[PDB]
Image (cartoon, coloured by chain):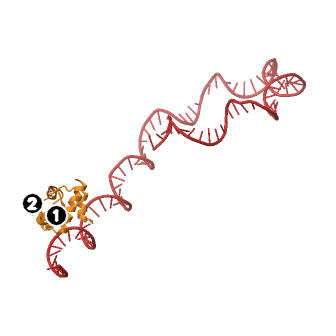
Amino acid sequence: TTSQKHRDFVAEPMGEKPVGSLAGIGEVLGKKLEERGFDKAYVVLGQFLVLKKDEDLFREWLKDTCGANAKQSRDCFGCLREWCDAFL
DNA sequence: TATGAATTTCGCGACACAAGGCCTGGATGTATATATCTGACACGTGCCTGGAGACTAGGGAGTAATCCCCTTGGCGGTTAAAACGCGGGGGACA
């Protein structure tokens, strides 16, 4: 259902977690995202909120911004959406 | 395109690490022991007045006869008090 990384990210507010803290976002993808400018997880979330929490927008943008497959982009969107439901 | 490859991300074991629960001992105040002195504790003496002994009085006190009386003892009934059940709501309790 959910990755343990996803559950850990969901359980608490993100605060200042790096983009690598996102579920399905490891060293390589998180590093690529930081190179693209979204150096922080909350920057990526602001992008996600600007996309009006859209799954397709966020996942396709993530895929074209770091190279994540459907799995990693889907996990990242799910993590962001569930965190938004929990705290936002 | 179906297959492999790549890639990656989540799940897994060894390692070292630190924090908490008994074991132990020593510093800690308390009870034990002991030398010093000093005026009270006790001892002992002279005495005289209270204690001890004899004689008397008589009135207090023990004891028997009597009354009555009142205190013990029993019955009926009529209760009004006492006994028992209940609901509570307010007081004692934490």
| Marks 2 & 1, CB-CB < 8 Å contact | no
Residue A83 in sight from this viewpoint: yes
Label 2 and label 1: CA atoms lie apart by: 17 Å
Is residue B33 shown above or below B14? above
Q: If you read the primary sequence from the N terminus, does the residue marked by circle 2 or circle 1 appear first?
A: 2
Secondary element type, mark 1? helix
Judging depth in this view, the residue of A18 and A54 nearest the camera is A54
Residue A82 numbered mark, or none: none
Kindly indicate which chain is depicted in orange in the rendered structure.
A
Look at label 2 and name its amino acid: Gly
Give the residue drawn at x 22%, y 61%.
A79
When asked about the image quadrant of residue B12, the answer is bottom left
Residue that numbered label 2 is attached to:
A37
Above or below, A78 against B46 in this view is below
* Viewer-proximal residue among A24 and B56: A24
> How far across and how far down the image is residue B73, in percent?
81, 34
Image colour assigned to chain B: red
The local crowd at label 1, few if under 14, some if 14 to 19, many if 20 or more residues have their Cα within 10 Å, is many
- Circle 1 residue: A59
Q: Chain of mark 2?
A: A
Residue B87, position in %: x, y? 55, 40
A27 to the left or right of B25: left
Give SS at disc 2: loop
Quarter location, residue B22: bottom left
Q: Residues within 10 Å of mark 2 (few under 14, many from 20)?
A: few
Measuring from the top left, give residue B35's x and y in whole percent: 42, 45
For the N terminus of chain A, give its image quadrant: bottom left
Q: Nearer the viewer, mark 2 or mark 1?
A: 1
Which one is nearer the viewer's eye here, A2 or B54?
A2
